[PDB]
Amino acid sequence: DPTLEWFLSHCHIHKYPSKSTLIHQGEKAETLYYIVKGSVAVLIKDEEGKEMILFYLNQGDFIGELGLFEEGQERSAWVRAKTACEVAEISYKKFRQLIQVNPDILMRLSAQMARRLQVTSEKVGNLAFLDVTGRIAQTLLNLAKQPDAMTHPDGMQIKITRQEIGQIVGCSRETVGRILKMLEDQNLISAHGKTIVVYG
Amino acid sequence: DPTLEWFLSHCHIHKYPSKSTLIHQGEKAETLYYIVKGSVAVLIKDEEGKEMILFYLNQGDFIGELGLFEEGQERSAWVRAKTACEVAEISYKKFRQLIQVNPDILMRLSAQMARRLQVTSEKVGNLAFLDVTGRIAQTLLNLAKQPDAMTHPDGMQIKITRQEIGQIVGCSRETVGRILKMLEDQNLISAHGKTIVVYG
Ligand SMILES: Nc1ncnc2c1ncn2[C@@H]1O[C@@H]2COP(=O)(O)O[C@H]2[C@H]1O
Ligand SMILES: Nc1ncnc2c1ncn2[C@@H]1O[C@@H]2COP(=O)(O)O[C@H]2[C@H]1O
Image (cartoon, rainbow over all chains, first blue to last red; front, side, top):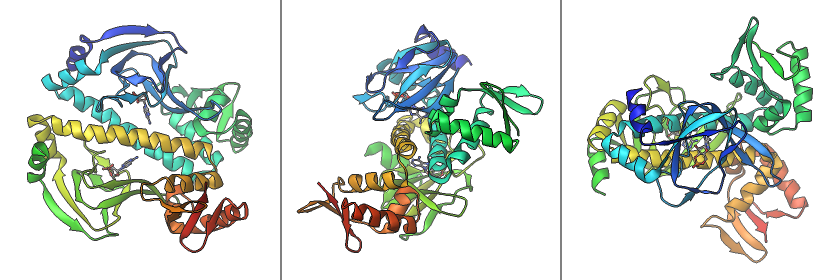
């Protein structure tokens, strides 16, 4: 996109090794980010530092946008490199000015925001209205519909530990274990190690 | 405000009686809304038509924004007049043009979006980490910490039907019933009708 390359040329680019943290919750938000390459997890934690994956973001996604519209706010979640990443960065001050030149940039951002809101609402709905078996089932679908969802002859094919799922659904890797076996008995999936086969 | 009366003068204004539905989930999203007066609930339902209040929006809040950034989408939730309302309305087509004249309007929208995303993410935390009893307990605290939370000699004091709680937590008024009694046995609250006493 020629409009992204306009945006990007005003950004400093920094590579982050898989597993490194780009954003720490609670920091002061003063900068926007943009994933040029790679993917990251958005996480939040609970009292005893228990993690919950709240979204996966990927190349082309902005990050750190939520403190852009009002000065003096804090990062609302940790963002962690899922794989090695290359992330552009820019101060909100500089970015607000781009918007002044070309509003189309703010338009691109708002669109990802509107979509994260839909998805997150749906996630809210999922926790309220599904049994932990139901969520784990939903989570597999959504994972096999990730841009990076691979392909298998009997459906889609994903990789993910039982703990990651556990964090996505808010259950333990133990519970995730039982339910994965159960869904496999119902021949809905197939688990050979850390590779699940979802059908669709 | 100068920008906002500009926005509004391009809108048709319609009054909605308390309890009437402004947006039906699944409809095609082609129009933006703006609450000139009153408040509404955003709800989603489950398989057996069970409701979950997902947000309260009020005078000054836009509604129906989530299908604005991509043509051909569906209302992501029902929006229902909490009290009698007066809601401006405008087609997305007209609104995209305003943005072209003055981007500041898209800037006001994005800000409410960024805040709904923070709040909704927060709510996802609770749902993941709190069972039906835990949530109902949390909900009472938060309610007794409302600006309008009254005072009692043994703690705070609130008013709310069991159904309202049911909607806050995504459970039925029946379930809310059991759990309220249970919490009362644990002498954590006291329910004499539609007035609960949370202790401390
Ligand atoms: N529900 C969500 N969906 C997607 N991304 C999110 C969500 N909540 C927070 N984030 C991202 O997490 C980032 C961390 O801090 P910010 O709030 O500054 O910017 C945030 C957003 O980019
Ligand atoms: N998580 C949420 N927080 C706040 N408002 C929401 C949320 N999810 C949906 N809405 C509102 O529900 C409206 C119904 O359809 P739209 O998606 O067009 O626009 C929606 C938003 O205004």
